[PDB]
Image 1: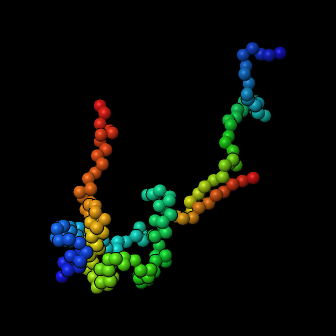
Image 2: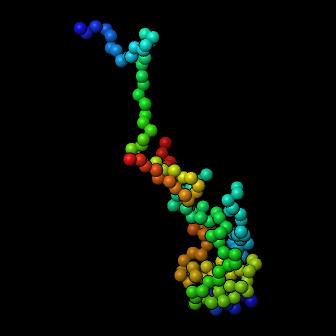
Image 3: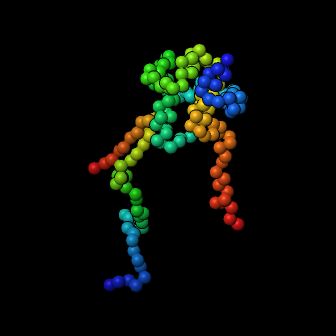
Length: 126
Length: 48
């Protein structure tokens, strides 16, 4: 049913490629809430301030503060992506929304085929 | 009159014991001292 919205947003020439990439990279990179308590070494201090800020539980709210300042008004798949989608299709819609923004920007939507800067042309002497 | 071999640098005790001394690093610091007591809590101790 999302092909209606995705043909509203972009052509049907790089469409199911976008769909399969968003599906497998959303089911691959799905992130839960993992740990980070102070009952369990040191990074750079500019990041360590925020890290030991985020270690404690009193700096976090008990329930999620929903966003208020309205963004993404050209692409209003967010209107369902707020709370109609919460399982795998939420991150699937997020990934295809990023792909739609990249392909309307006219640039590569993947990150695997953004190929590495090979640095062993500077460090291959002797 | 200078005795031509002795360099000295010693003290004679009350029991004719030769006492010699080393140099010691002072406890007072010329730069202030930084410390991390608990994370995101820091200490800067100086002296005058």
